[PDB]
Length: 220
Length: 214
Length: 15
Ligand SMILES: O=P(O)(O)OC[C@H](O)CO
Ligand SMILES: O=P(O)(O)OC[C@H](O)CO
Ligand SMILES: [NH3+]C1CCCCC1
Ligand SMILES: [NH3+]C1CCCCC1
Ligand SMILES: [NH3+]C1CCCCC1
Image (cartoon, rainbow over all chains, first blue to last red; front, side, top):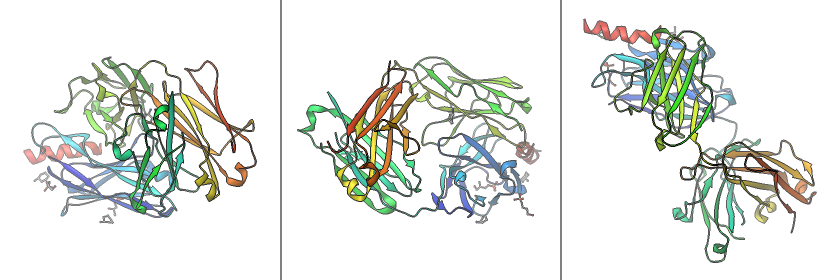
């Protein structure tokens, strides 16, 4: 079986260059085409280019020609994407993808189409520094309550309620990027009004990069 | 460059319904080198069809591809719950490979008006010198909804951000949260904070509001 | 087509 494992998320300053790696195991590394595909947040897939390692032949999309380099190292079965002169519009998840093969096994006739995908690498182009969030209550028929997780960097934060015991009616929204360059995220839950006096609601917020781990009791 | 057009960009369909997704190319795709991918939120794309009509082993045979030249179709014979996702076509008949913009197949359900809630800024946040006012639009369908902020009846622009959840896996609704942000000083200059909501399920706009400091 | 190159590599490894 073919497995593609990419390097981890990285924050890059505007104007800098990023290198993303893709280590392959299984099948043949040198005789199958390896491509890079990116996806900006909330947008579609975009093919950037590829390499055939045995022949050291690259193929770049015109809109990246002059700004990217793709290379392959047969000794480690690793492929690399370099993207230069980074701008905010380059913030995206970058995927490596290898063409599939027909028949049994993974050494058959190549199919061109991308059967094997890496897990993706989030590249965030930003001038922001690591910062932990503040956690503010959204104080409460049906009642709504929640937590506002404001001003953190980088992604992600995770939120649970009552240590995971409460999931019904929970909505945790996608983060938004503020003009400051910091993220904000809201999580809400609806509960019976009658439960407000006789039940505690606690939002559990985790931001690993800042070691912010807060359990915020939300009351009327 | 071959431009691939996937129209409509969204299809609202019922569980168990047949789905047909179109991919039209600006010119003939060499050797039917056309593929289809599925992508669910937070996951890498997955190959469903290559060479216009070939299906890899392991891919469910309710997915079938057809077409040639410029006109291609992905057919899903009967939508399973896991089939609600985004589908992309891709051509690789030229050295410049391109993707369609994607079609989201989402769950059709009955109309549900948003339940609206407004939250003043916490005392804790106000101590820090900033005021975030939050408006929640909960459990509505279809996805199209609009929020406007009014402060002492003055329509606000440029000081709010919003986001929307993925379709709920249980009841197939959406929710939306919008946050109005002001400095403490500016927040304290005004009395009435209101969010005004419009939606297909509403015959007239719904306004939720509070008076600062009550 | 760059996409066709590995097919030929496969073919000439056979023969
Ligand atoms: O390049 P090959 O054909 O020698 O095979 C490389 C191995 O598959 C290592 O992934
Ligand atoms: O990145 P490429 O495809 O332009 O390759 C660089 C050349 O091999 C250097 O002469
Ligand atoms: N490991 C190296 C591969 C691409 C060039 C720079 C890093
Ligand atoms: N209609 C498409 C919008 C961007 C990618 C997902 C589907
Ligand atoms: N002798 C084989 C080596 C790899 C390319 C195809 C032929």
